[PDB]
Length: 107
Length: 129
Length: 114
Image 1 (cartoon, rainbow over the protein chains, first blue to last red):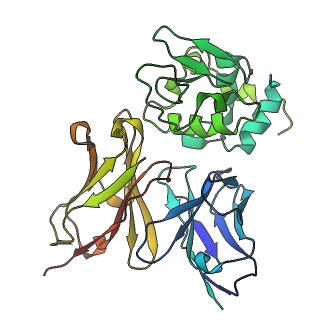
Image 2: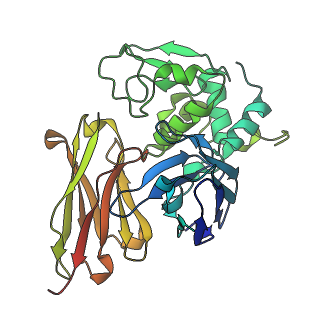
Image 3: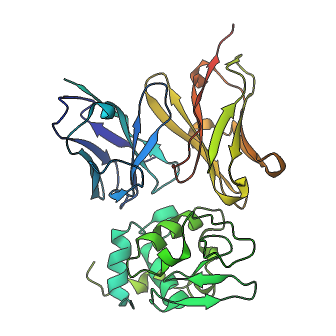
């Protein structure tokens, strides 16, 4: 199974500042890496699909980059509504797998 | 837009088709060759009233909505016009959903008839990738 | 538009079959690929499997063949059956379409001898 490793496990930031979250795959997955946001008592929300493709209805401050084994999700000017969990998921090979997640919180 | 063989191979690699769902890159380049002859604007009207669109000839009865096909299901949740772009993004996104079904690449008739069983790797050979 | 919603028991006993239903409203289940995902207590997500338009299914090997995903057009719902559950199956279960743009609200299912 493809293993996705996310870092940092936790990241504290002050609203207004920007951050970048990492997701590394155990083997190449091309551009088949997706990003999800998840808050308590809520289901996951797709933010970026296929490494860098934007999603209608998602804030423009979210952007994705990367290919192969190294990917990143960037948030330009974090807002309070952005604190929560972030997970990457690969669909290059079944079973689809998720990274361990990165928690974004107010510093 | 009419893609060059190597030009499409490189693009499809960028779009993550190499090994997706267990299918090597050569399969996709070969499929495009026989489905549309590398032409992103290719369209073909079918008997059931549906139309095949784009570089990978995606059907309007099952995959995309062109608003002119009887029992359209729009499995790819996308307008067929998006599959007629010189930008292959939408066609690749949809092709990945199509191939994820148990039928795999058999959904592409030209691929079945002219690619399956052949040395598909030859389609990406001799290219700067 | 499309709405998804999970329903089923929130408490099950070890060794029994956990069965969940996902009701789809707004369009036919015959127009998409349907999935089941779960989140374990450690903030760990697992893609359980999905069923495509042809009926073909993909199940996570981690489930050791304990899972079954079926559909019912007449009622526009799809299901999740997970047999021989253990306390290891305690989790929040979610139904969502394959594209990941439509998700249920998630439902916590606890496996306990009580």
